Length: 93
Length: 95
Length: 32
Length: 32
Image (cartoon, rainbow over all chains, first blue to last red; front, side, top):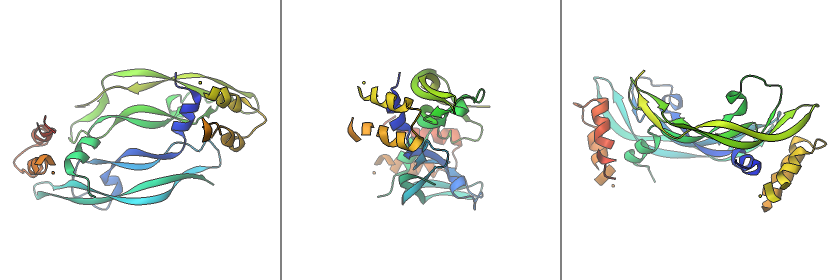
């Protein structure tokens, strides 16, 4: 049984690897198709354990990945993309 | 320092990953009590099958047990253990 | 373990509030 | 970067399909 202390510590609000849809991060073009269609990103996770507190990113950076953009029957190219990452998270009103 | 395509593919490809799930989602019923923490870390299926006709499902699964505070507001708060389902394996399968 | 002890007795204190108890346990996590 | 070489070249193959291409990168994921 995992101890309350470890559950509390490990689940408390903090940046965690999160698999995000590229289409959610780029709704503007549903024209292409991306391989992989989802990407790992450090994002805010956990709970602040308060009613009146939410978890927001404080520090944010930019990561760059090689992804396949694929236009069906029109051809497919490989390139770089930039995604947002969360370097720090805080519990705030 | 740009991450290579192969590593992006491998790391985002379908697999069990740590996932913070709200306890109220694992127990939609009841809801008389309140849970501290309000969310708990659980291995779940994540990623993409990179196919149109495939979805990612858990094939093998176990049970993890955690010490959580169950709290009835103004009625008191006690500590106990709860069991959640975790995913030990995931695969890409049709639908 | 005495650490997880402290963290449980903290959590059982009715006369506390979320943020005070939060502080109290995150002393036992700051240390242990 | 050889392993990643093969992994990009495979992915650029138009005449392949999702599941065949998949196999090919995973032949290089069979090695690296």
